[PDB]
Image (cartoon, coloured by chain):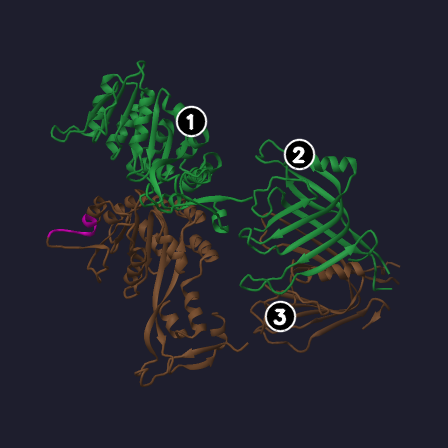
Chain colours: A green, B brown
Amino acid sequence: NHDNFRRLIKRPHGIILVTGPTGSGKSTTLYAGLQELNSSERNILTVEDPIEFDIDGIGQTQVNPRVDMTFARGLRAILRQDPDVVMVGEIRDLETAQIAVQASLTGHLVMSTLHTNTAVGAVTRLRDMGIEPFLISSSLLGVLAQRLVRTLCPDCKEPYEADKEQRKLFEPLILYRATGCPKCNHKGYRGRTGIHELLLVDDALQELIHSEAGEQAMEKHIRATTPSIRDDGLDKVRQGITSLEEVMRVTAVDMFIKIGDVKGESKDKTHAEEIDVLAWSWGMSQSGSMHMAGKVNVQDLSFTKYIDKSTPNLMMACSSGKHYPQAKLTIRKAGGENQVEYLIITLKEVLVSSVSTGGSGGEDRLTENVTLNFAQVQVDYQPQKADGAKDGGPVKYGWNIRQNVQA
Amino acid sequence: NHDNFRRLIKRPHGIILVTGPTGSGKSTTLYAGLQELNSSERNILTVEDPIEFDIDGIGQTQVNPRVDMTFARGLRAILRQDPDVVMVGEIRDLETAQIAVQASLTGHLVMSTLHTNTAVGAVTRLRDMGIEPFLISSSLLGVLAQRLVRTLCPDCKEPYEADKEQRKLFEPLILYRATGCPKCNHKGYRGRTGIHELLLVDDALQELIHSEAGEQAMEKHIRATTPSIRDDGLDKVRQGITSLEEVMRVTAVDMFIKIGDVKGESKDKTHAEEIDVLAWSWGMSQSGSMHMAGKVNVQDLSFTKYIDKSTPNLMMACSSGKHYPQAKLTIRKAGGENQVEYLIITLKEVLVSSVSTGGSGGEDRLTENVTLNFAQVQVDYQPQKADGAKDGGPVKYGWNIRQNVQA
């Protein structure tokens, strides 16, 4: 986060905003940014209301209402001093933002703040005041959504294993609790630390601002690249700096398959390190007829998957012709890990009959089809009631294909 | 509904509206929400016109016209008191809504009301006053459409079985009637209770507000997730709290198949615990020619179905090659259980010739195709008149395929 912020505040021009609620340590972050830039090779000037403290080596004008010296008039005056970087206390109105946008386009690096709850809230807020949707895309370098969280006192904090609902937010996973004590005096914390979410405007985000995709569409692309405010907080909870209580206050059927001991890349909590199934197909046919006995012909179980770390292992098994002891396809209802696994197809003595892979120039994640030949098969369907609870036990179908008998 | 409302009013920021007509108990619901939040860790302030009653521990300013203290000016003053949560009496005009939208974006949780008949009516109403379509998506957490319904007195209420038109709104289904009596004094009710519809703005609803899908499109997605106002009322009618009269004032061919004694998962009243048929196909061909005899070739009856509790049993029958005594495909006109079963295809000595199952990553309910070989077949079509009544008896077609003769 520092290296990304370093590079951003060291650009020749553009706007960099720091957002969040009151008492989130925005000024402290800006002051630290200006002190880092504070060199003999740059001319740094600021308009503030009021000046928090004095940085030696940097000019700092104060918003004076006695002479009608406002943020807009102060910022308009600073631009005639030949500045390289400018720091505006905050851009409350359109007039001040208009000058800051012009400043950013005219070879100056601008810095300011906005009282918005999210990093998208800052881009939002500029669109609200009346800055043309374009002007934000051209000028804006990035946004820094910041919160402060109280630091658990290291002398008296209580270790505890997290519950299921807590573990779902993030193998003994120990978090830490508040408590209270004489240095603790007598709360669970002493001091503070910042948690961040650095939105960095790249080529993709420059389009979404221009064409007005929207908060949601823009939030979807933002989560693909940048970590959230909560995720940065949860990392500090793992490290043992702040509590989970402190981070939170300031803040289609699923299908898997496990072939032997071959590990995939599933992010599922229960089905971790398995192969994510995108689709599947399997069947059987009886040759016997009632118009006059026959025999069953069980097909190979096909299934689609992403090209993951199991891809070479399945190719090796297909090439060598070595079979796995067991393979278990698991289907599950929509909701999460606690939902009912309503269909589980277990296979025994499993070969990899074929692997079909490839890709196109438009696909972000490439897929491949894999078929599985097997000696035995067991299908376990679990019926459910109207409310979602399990209706009795699971209905079983078992068959030995090698010996042609029930199993 | 309480747990969902709890989590919503305990968010760090956003607008939560309670809507409905006059005398729907909105204030009572807001007051209950503020009392639940009323803690020492939060600063709660309110602007009201007038103040309904005093919550001890919460600040409550009144709209005074003698000093020109309005909702807008009062809300604008409250925001300078460093509040965590704010409750505005109601947002009647644009100016008051503009401040509430800014308040929600600037780290405050806002609460208010709007006189709209539906939960979509609230989102509607904000778009009408002149709030930019976006600003609603970013700020709005949810809407609570609320009505009050009179409670049937438990000492004197009359049990009665509902009629067809009444049963269609929602196996002896008994509802309760008003009546009148000395505690009943002398109406059918004493006291009241609230019925609700909690619209919860999620990622999908954030798009529909942004891109302006519309009331209808938005109402369609809302019915997929959240229960209606009427459904919450009808649940209380089943419980025996209020009458059906009180809730209302404030407010393709069906195909089944039964294979032997194998139970499916049909929710139909007449065809209960049978297999729901999605589609089917069956045919026959005669080799005889008039250009010069031949023989009939009856095909296997294919049909589509969901993956239900019968799936393993059909796979076992296909694998073992054991035939059922009878299998009856039933087609029925659109309407319900009382409609005419206009096509019934009965099969005798039935094998399961094949089973083809599978699924994709987008499907919510997976389907599968099953074919049926049989010795005999009987098709019974029932003709109908223009009004819908049965036109005479059913026309029969019977044939023994094993012996190649009429049946």
- Residue at 40% in and 37% down: A212
Q: Looking at this view, is B5 or B293 the one in front?
A: B5
Q: Which one is earlier in the sequence, the residue at label 2 or at label 1?
A: 1
Residues drawn in magenta: B67-74
The x, y position of residue A76, in whole percent, is 22, 24
Left or right: B38, with A304 as reference point: left
Quadrant in which the C terminus of chain A appears: bottom right
Q: Nearer the viewer, mark 2 or mark 1?
A: 1
Say which mark, if any, is on residue A4: 1
Residues flagged by tags 3 and 2 on a common chain: no
Q: Which mark is residue B272?
A: 3
* Numbered badge on residue B378: none
Residue A105 percent location from the top left of the image: 33, 23
Q: Are marks 3 and 2 in contact (CB under 8 Å)?
A: no
Residue beneath disc 2: A358
Q: Residue furthest front?
A: A182
- Kind of residue at disc 1: Asn
Q: Chain of mark 2?
A: A
Q: Kindly report the distance in space between the C-alpha atoms of the residues bearing marks 2 and 1.
A: 36 Å
- Would you call the spot at circle 2 few (<14 residues within 10 Å), some (14-19), or many (20 or more)? few
Under mark 2, the amino acid is Gly
Residue A64 placement, left or right of A171 = left
Residue A62: where, in percent of width, then height? 19, 27
SS for dot 2: loop
What is the distance, in whole Å, between disc 3 and disc 2 at their CAs? 47 Å
Q: Chain of mark 1?
A: A
Circle 3: residue type: Ala
Q: Chain of mark 3?
A: B
| Distance from Cα at disc 1 to Cα at disc 3 | 63 Å
